[PDB]
Amino acid sequence: ATPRLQYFHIAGPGTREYLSEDLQQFISATGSYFDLKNKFRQTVVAPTRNVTTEKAQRLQIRFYPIQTDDTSTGYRVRYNINVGDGWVLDMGSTYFDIKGILDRGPSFKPYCGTAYNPLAPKESMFNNWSETAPGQNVSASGQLSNVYTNTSTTKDTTAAQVTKISGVFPNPNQGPGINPLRQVENANTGVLGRFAKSQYNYAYGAYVKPVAADGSQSLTQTPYWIMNNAGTEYLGAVAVEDYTNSLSYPDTMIVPPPEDYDDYNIGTTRALRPNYIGFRDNFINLLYHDSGVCSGTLNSERSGMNVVVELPDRNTELSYQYMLADMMSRHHYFALWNQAVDQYDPEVRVFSNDGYEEGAPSYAFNPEAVGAGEGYGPDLSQIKLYTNNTAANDKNTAVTNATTNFYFGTVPSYEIDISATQRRNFIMANIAEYLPDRYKFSISGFDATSVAPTTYEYMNKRVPLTNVVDMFTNVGARWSIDQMDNVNPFNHHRNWGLKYRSQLLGNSRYVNFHIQVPQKFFAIKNLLLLSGSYTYEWVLRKDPNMILQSSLGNDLRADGASIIYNEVNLMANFMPMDHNTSNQLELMLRNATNDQTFVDYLGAKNALYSVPAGSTALTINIPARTWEGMRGWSFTRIKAAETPQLGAQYDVNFKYSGSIAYSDGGFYLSHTFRNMSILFDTSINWPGNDRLLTPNMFEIKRSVALDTEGFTMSQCDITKDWYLIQMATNYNFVYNGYRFWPDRQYFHYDFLRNFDPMTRQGPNFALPGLFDLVSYTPTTDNSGEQPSQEAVRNNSGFIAPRSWPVWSAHQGESWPANWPYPLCGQQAIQPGQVLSYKKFLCDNYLWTIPFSSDFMYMGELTDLGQNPMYTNNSHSMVINFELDPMDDPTYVYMLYGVFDTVRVNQPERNVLAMAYFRTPFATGNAV
Amino acid sequence: TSINWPGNDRLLTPNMFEIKRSVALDTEGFTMSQCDITKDWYLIQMATN
């Protein structure tokens, strides 16, 4: 351009063509050790024509609904996407601008613990006052902190404070105000206090809403004078306020003792379980995908024929999950699409018990350094000091007056091992509370069958058994709690993805949410719409269980959750390219030979096969079929209670609000898969070439205890054959050697990223010794007492009794522990009294078996998928599964390998036509 | 004194680069990514970067 600009290489020719050829050869040859390319400048220049219109064209267009039909299960919206000539719409830029009111219900705690007197001890009381009538039979217990240096024997100095009582003056926040507590004379100190007469005396979690603008939780205060046994000696005064009906305990629940201790013991109070009710990852289950009854609609006006056809056997939202996880790492939190992957804390799931950081003995000392707590030794209180005589080596002269404290011993202190305190609190709060309901018991005020197990206060008022999980539970083994490894780990308050998603809405259950939801259906997920007038209808879910995710998985419909949609607009971004260039573009995309073609990323027909609780085996029969281009198999097992009805507008049997492992990638039951077999004909096994070490089945895992010949890989119970197949599928190289593949560690759904082999040893019970003191079965009684837990005697006088609830106050006496049998050390049990428990966990993996001759990837259209023996011949393959028996009805999420592809034909203006074809499992009915 | 640089009805508010707006005062949307940043500003930043 400008010679002035070409001089400075701002618009010049370019480094390749202004540098002398010999210099270019030099800087290319000597470019690995002495760089010179950074010293010469070349500028990339914009096309400056035929890239943007001068015409006034909106850069971002909002489409507000034509026609709504607000209903009580969904929220339909219909738009008229008018794309003029010279315009071009990429539907990847089309998203729903949704705002409304969200109610997350009473079952929503965005925070562990409480906000009301958190530092208060759990069993403390807020300076009680129990009376039948004012001035009648009265019981009161509390601290009297305020002082007013009274001159006793008269009311002159006490009545002055009494007249001030009728306000905020007692001021429970303020105390004595003196740091050295030894300087007070007990006869000229004055005493004041402020007590509350109410039911449910507990300091922890106590809340009384204010009535005046300056504290003042009550309006009427009745003062009471403090005198000794005689009435003449005036000592102090007390403020008493009625909180009988003005007091409440939000976010806290009373943990009463067993019924035998209901009286004479108020137990402790505990904060409710923390529950996060934010939206789901990537706004999953917020648009009605794959539901024929409430399917979306996209079509032109001239031909009002829908082009989006949805199938109940496809999974659009899991497809988007897999697509996004392959496109980027899942640890990136993109707050726009609510892109926060559901992740469990590994320190909670794969429990690596290690005790605690044992350091020097740690003590909490007196606030001052002088005290007589447990006043052993000489009293040292009425002593007298005489000065020393060096010559006589004895006392010589008395000290006239010596006000001395002079206590005995070191600083009074109480020893706490906070390193183990954190460990126990962590275990009980994270791993113990999230135990299955079969390892819990009521609290002597709660009763089962009076409320659904899927409710909030059911989970809150059921204390887990305290010996199934504790600090001695596999004290040195990195071992997930086998009583809980079948529990969805993503239903946890440590779900950082869910925590972030629930924190994006706010800190209350009354949310005026404003969200943007993308279109995930693969045919129009990123379709480029040409010119024409199209109508684009969709319906938004209003099911509280589906749209919202809980960290507890409780039934939100029974928990008052609801949502209201006010404005649902359709945003779009239009590139302002030149009408000449956009007209050329649309002319060349209206040509038949080159037209948009999209395949769903999952590429799987999704079939759910029910497996009841007791069943350990599953037989899958598929009738005669053409298996053309079928990619392979993929499968996990999903709990039935955690999976909605496929293609149902509203599921009433779905009383779960955690992580639907079907909808998202939150798979956690890839284990509990004993083996598998595939038989294309009635008896012809698929590998069927002596490939595997077990030729006629896919032995996924075998117990090492019964293992004798080997056939187990990677220091767990997985087999050689299965490990080989999985590594060959995921990484394509097993015949040149097994190795780690860090190129796929971002995927969040591959094998090595989340395959965790485990090994614990454990005592060998069913021996003359080794009595197995841990009882895993509760007594399923109303009383909050579990006497079967009283056999462990560990931390006897320093924790709550095992029969008592976990979070009750401590009582007992110090005693040698008896339960944890030493598996290490010099006094360990004999080698014949230990066992082996090789096990593996594999979350979010979705076992894959590729329909390839050698289990390795040679193209999306597999080796055997195009073989003219499955494609042309009809085969009726039979799958036989063997599973670990679970304790609830579970599906087996089976995924085949399909080419569910669509190519979009847009020959003229407002003519939109789509052809859907799925190679193994087509849906053409020839009508 | 009369030439808006976008000046072609580009932004949802053609006459200014509305960086953020009060969601309480909001009526028609124009707030993006679950905060008070605007659709136009979000588009501009994402396109630039």
Image (cartoon, coloured by chain):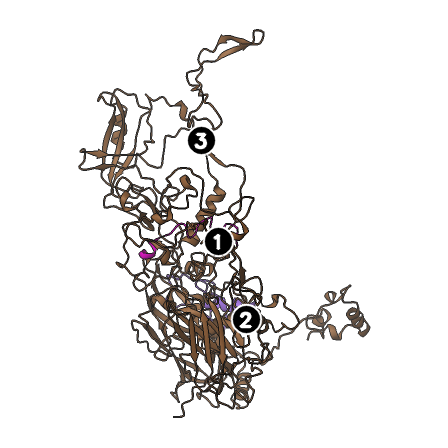
Chain colours: A brown, B purple
Q: Secondary structure at mark 2?
A: helix
Mark drawn on residue A764:
1
Q: What is the spatial separation of the Cα atoms under label 2 and label 3, in whole angstroms? A: 59 Å
Q: Nearer the viewer, mark 1 or mark 3?
A: 1
Q: Secondary structure at mark 3?
A: loop
Q: Magenta span covers which residues?
A: A457-477
Against A720, residue A829 (above or below) is above
Label 1 neighbour load within 10 Å: few <14, some 14-19, many 20+: some
Horizontal relation, residue A670 to residue A167: left or right: right
Across and down, in percent, residue A823 comes to: 52, 49
Q: Is residue A469 magenta?
A: yes
Q: What is the spatial separation of the Cα atoms under label 1 and label 3, in whole angstroms? A: 48 Å
Across and down, in percent, residue A855 comes to: 58, 76
- CB within 8 Å, label 2 to label 1: no
Give me the chain letter of mark 1. Answer: A
Magenta segment's dominant SS is loop
- Of labels 2 and 1, earlier in sequence is 2
Q: What is the spatial separation of the Cα atoms under label 2 and label 1, in whole angstroms? A: 48 Å
Do we see residue A102 in this rendering? Answer: yes
User: Which residue is the site of mark 2?
Assistant: A327
> Which residue ends up furthest to the front in the rendered image?
A768
Label 3 neighbour load within 10 Å: few <14, some 14-19, many 20+: some
**In the figure, residue A172 lies in which quadrant?**
top left
The quadrant of the picture occupied by the C terminus of chain A is: bottom left
Q: Is residue A783 magenta?
A: no
- Of labels 2 and 3, earlier in sequence is 2
The quadrant of the picture occupied by the N terminus of chain A is: bottom right
